[PDB]
Length: 174
Ligand SMILES: Cc1cc(-c2nnn[nH]2)ccc1-c1cc(=O)c(O)c(C(=O)O)[nH]1
Ligand SMILES: [Mn+2]
Ligand SMILES: [Mn+2]
Image 1 (cartoon, rainbow, N blue to C red):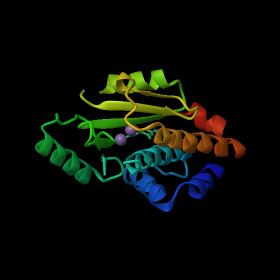
Image 2 (image 1 turned 30 degrees about the horizontal axis):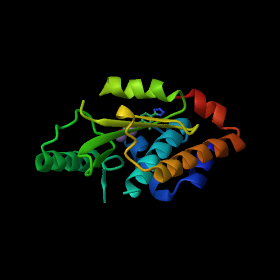
Image 3 (image 1 turned 180 degrees about the vertical axis):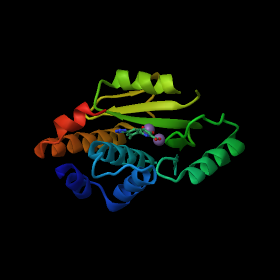
Image 4 (image 1 turned 120 degrees about the vertical axis):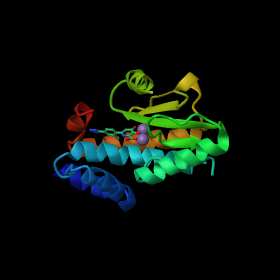
């Protein structure tokens, strides 16, 4: 599968390995669920990029669950902020709030609603592969250059997938 090779070529081994671990520990073969694999990589990367543009952020995503909950818990006890129900993606020490990051192949408002419906003090920031984003109260957290870098990376993933005729498949599997 070119999709599997593409992921190998375009994300760095840590992201790939982290994504593989996540899949394989819950019994999902990344060689069969190749679109899932690519999405998990994409989303991890966005999450890592977003933290890197700060340390302003605590990365919650990509840790094993024990660690993620340890981190979340340690944040709740030292700040007073409510413990989210699910693991969010980041903690913002400047705005003192968790962030859930969304990456979508569909309309950003659509994905934003799904996340907001699923979530309750958590800040939501959705990115698309089109350069669109949407964020709680139109507060985008990052500065424009960091956001522009995320969107550039995401648009380049799309185009790479499209160079390899994987984009149509990838787009319809969200
Ligand atoms: C990246 C991803 C892909 C899939 C998926 N399932 N099938 N294809 N992609 C499901 C959930 C997630 C996902 C998205 C998130 O934004 C997110 O914060 C998480 C998470 O589990 O914390 N998972
Ligand atoms: Mn997450
Ligand atoms: Mn997320």
